[PDB]
Amino acid sequence: GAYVLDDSDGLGREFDGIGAVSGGGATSRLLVNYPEPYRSEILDYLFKPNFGASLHILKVEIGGDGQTTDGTEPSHMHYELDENYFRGYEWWLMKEAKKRNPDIILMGLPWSFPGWLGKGFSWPYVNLQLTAYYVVRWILGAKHYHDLDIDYIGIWNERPFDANYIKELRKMLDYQGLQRVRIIASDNLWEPISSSLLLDQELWKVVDVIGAHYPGTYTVWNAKMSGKKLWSSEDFSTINSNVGAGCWSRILNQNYINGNMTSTIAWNLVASYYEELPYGRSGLMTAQEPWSGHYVVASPIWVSAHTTQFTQPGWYYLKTVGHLEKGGSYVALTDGLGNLTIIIETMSHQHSMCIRPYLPYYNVSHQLATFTLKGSLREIQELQVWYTKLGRLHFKQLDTLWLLDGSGSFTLELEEDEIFTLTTLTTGRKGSYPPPPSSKPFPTNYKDDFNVEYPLFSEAPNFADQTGVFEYYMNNEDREHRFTLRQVLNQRPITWAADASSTISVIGDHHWTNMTVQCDVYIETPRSGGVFIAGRVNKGGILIRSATGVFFWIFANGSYRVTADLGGWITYASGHADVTAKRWYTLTLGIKGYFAFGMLNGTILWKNVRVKYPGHGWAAIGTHTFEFAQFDNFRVEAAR
Ligand SMILES: *[C@@H]1O[C@H](CO)[C@@H](O[C@@H]2O[C@H](CO)[C@@H](O)[C@H](O)[C@H]2NC(C)=O)[C@H](O)[C@H]1NC(C)=O
Ligand SMILES: *[C@@H]1O[C@H](CO)[C@@H](O[C@@H]2O[C@H](CO)[C@@H](O)[C@H](O)[C@H]2NC(C)=O)[C@H](O)[C@H]1NC(C)=O
Ligand SMILES: *[C@@H]1O[C@H](CO)[C@@H](O[C@@H]2O[C@H](CO)[C@@H](O)[C@H](O)[C@H]2NC(C)=O)[C@H](O)[C@H]1NC(C)=O
Ligand SMILES: *[C@@H]1O[C@H](CO)[C@@H](O)[C@H](O)[C@H]1NC(C)=O
Ligand SMILES: *[C@@H]1C[C@@H](O)[C@@H](O)[C@@H](CO)O1
Ligand SMILES: [Ca+2]
Image (tube, rainbow, N blue to C red; front, side, top):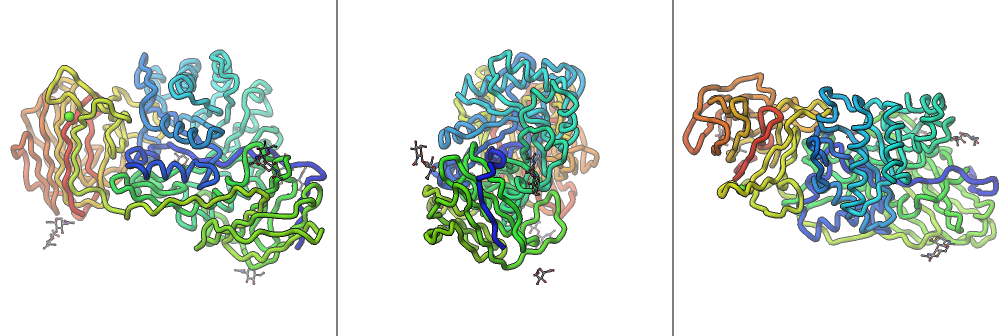
């Protein structure tokens, strides 16, 4: 009926901010080669204050060379004694975010680790100090090379923590002058981190935040008892239609109301990875076409604004938040300076399901809500009003509300699938840029000679690595192949996902069905070495081991194979070829209907080999194991 908002008996918890994740894995891959001005516009919609999503927090993967959901991300230490703080795109992204919002909060978290840290095992806790050394390197490099202060460091994404590791990490951070960096643990479930903190005083002192994933708006008693800040450090992960926007809206409010969580962080920041990779289009917005410039300011962007434009980390929740009589919820926050923000959500069940967890039915129906401002809020006479309706009307500023009759009270008619933000703040804005170009499929003729002497990013555009890591490579000692693309892992990472046994990078249009792929290849390992080119590759990311298609392999022992699968279990054709290590060969693979052919140096090696049809997927290149190999003069022409 009536809902009292009041600060006379004190405040609720401090609000820590809303954010999103770039990484786990390569979710920002296709954003880097957007042409201007579109790249900058996308970044504004994400990070520019009083504009779009206006995010408070950016969390990024600390790349570990392993597959981490939609690709691999490059590590700062591929090998022992290797350090490089200019690989990948997270450095660039953090700097772009910081340029727009100097007060943005930055977080790092590893999903995978380079294999050498395991000292013979696929386990990062074999040598605690070595693993902590590696992670602290990353934080120091952020500061020294990019002028970035990392605010929070995590442990091992959705994988076991080791209490001694966490203690060693704190000790090493302090030793390296990073006392200001805080620790969040364990980026998995509420247990066992929560009970561990109650039983171990030394662990309790070193953990600043309990970060739990997909908590379904609830926490657990042990986490409440800890007295630590509680964050949903990975949530959302739902297609960014109106359904996803509804999920985001509902959990933004109710994570605090139901679970005492004062930060929620969406996976992922922006969908800039091929949509047919796992969890396609599950970012706050969509930018999956750098070749066209087409992007989509999806509804979750405006859902974010309803909170982010009108709150900041350091504000406090009131004690007076809760559910509405007929469904939906309200939170309220102040800044201790006289401002007040009220965020109301009435998300229907059928239009707000997150993928994790699925909620049993709950009813939402038309209702009236009367709010009465008691305490210091009574004095307020005026409120700006922002309104969104999902299904569609986004972030529309309505007529100001006047509180004149001394009552300190007001009333609203609420329907379903609505958001209202009522705030004293006058700074709100629905940021706008002209529409970007229409969507267009990946170019049906595409080439890359990798001839770039000082590349802005460490890898050629559009190549999305799914196992292994591929990089621009310069070889001064060669003229024709001075600039190539090289696979650089020489051992399997400490994996997070189930990486393939062969390295692979995919590119192009998953819809492609008939296609001709060509590439110069160079095998660096004598006798045992092998490489391939491929087409119709149908799966990647967390499922890269499942990939089928047509794979044309050549080996340094003078053999070739054509397979139906990346794992090489199924043979379409096999035979001998004049192929050795350390020599450049040109491979061609043509696929049309039921039949494929392969060329070696422009000469037919096999033809009219029967393959599964229909079938469709990306073009790809790769190596037999985790081994050095180079590629040059890539080309594909295709039809869908
Ligand atoms: C966590 O939030 C819960 C609410 O979800 C708080 O628990 C109580 O909530 C009921 C209604 O659900 C209120 O009537 C009580 O006033 C709340 N208790 C107290 C002591 O305020 C709880 O406060 C929060 N836990 C904390 C802050 O540790
Ligand atoms: C609401 O919040 C705004 C934003 O901080 C407050 O305005 C600022 O007040 C500080 C002093 O506390 C000044 O140094 C800033 O220059 C002000 N900024 C702007 C944009 O005005 C404001 O005082 C708060 N209270 C009310 C009633 O608006
Ligand atoms: C890919 O190639 C196959 C084989 O050439 C095409 O399938 C043929 O299409 C023609 C004309 O549409 C038909 O007359 C044939 O009977 C089809 N053959 C088979 C085996 O189905 C297919 O249309 C091509 N697809 C694209 C997108 O180019
Ligand atoms: C939801 O609640 C309203 C009012 O109580 C009721 O009329 C309606 O039938 C309910 N819907 C369902 C599916 O129970
Ligand atoms: C959290 C980790 C991230 O990389 C994704 O795998 C996501 C999928 O829902 O879960
Ligand atoms: Ca070249």
